[PDB]
Image: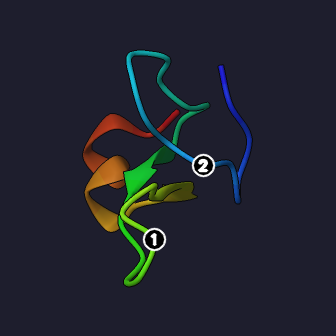
């Protein structure tokens, strides 16, 4: 699992509700609690 502010990439997954998200100039993305994560409340 990964924590918030953690660069995303290959298979790994984050710690709900944290989900791989995208930034801007860094497609790397980062694990951040997404609103849709509510439907899957960790």
Q: Label 2 crowding class (10 Å Cα cut-off): few <14, some 14-19, many 20+?
A: some
- Residue 41 versus residue 29 in the image, above or below: above
The location of residue 16, given as percent across then percent down, is: 54, 35
Total count of labels? 2
- Residue 10 versus residue 14 in the image, above or below: above
Q: Which residue is mark 1?
A: 26
The mark nearer the N terminus, 2 or 1, is 2
The location of residue 25, given as percent across then percent down, is: 41, 82
The location of residue 35, given as percent across then percent down, is: 34, 66
Question: Image check: 41 left or right of 30?
Answer: left
**Residue at far front of view:** 25
Please identify, in this view, whether the residue under mark 2 or under mark 1 is nearer the observer: 1
Residue sitting at x 70%, y 59%: 5
Residue sitting at x 74%, y 41%: 3
Residue sitting at x 44%, y 40%: 41
Quadrant position of residue 30: bottom right
Question: Image check: 9 left or right of 40?
Answer: right
- The quadrant of the picture occupied by the N terminus is top right
Q: Nearer the viewer, residue 36 or 4?
A: 4
Q: Nearer the viewer, residue 12 or 33?
A: 12
* Figure colour scheme: rainbow
Q: Which residue is mark 2?
A: 7
Q: CA distance from mark 2 to mark 1?
A: 9 Å
- Residue 13 versus residue 23 in the image, above or below: above
Q: Are marks 2 and 1 in contact (CB under 8 Å)?
A: yes
> For numbered disc 2, what is the local secondary structure?
loop
> For numbered disc 1, what is the local secondary structure?
loop
**Residue at far bottom of view:** 24
Q: Nearer the viewer, residue 25 or 22?
A: 25
Q: Label 1 crowding class (10 Å Cα cut-off): few <14, some 14-19, many 20+?
A: few
């Amino acid at each position: 699992c990964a924590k918030k502010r953690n660069w995303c990439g290959k298979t790994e997954d984050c710690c709900c509700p944290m989900k791989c998200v995208y930034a801007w100039y860094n497609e790397q993305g980062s694990c951040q609690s997404t609103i849709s994560a509510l439907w899957k409340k960790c």
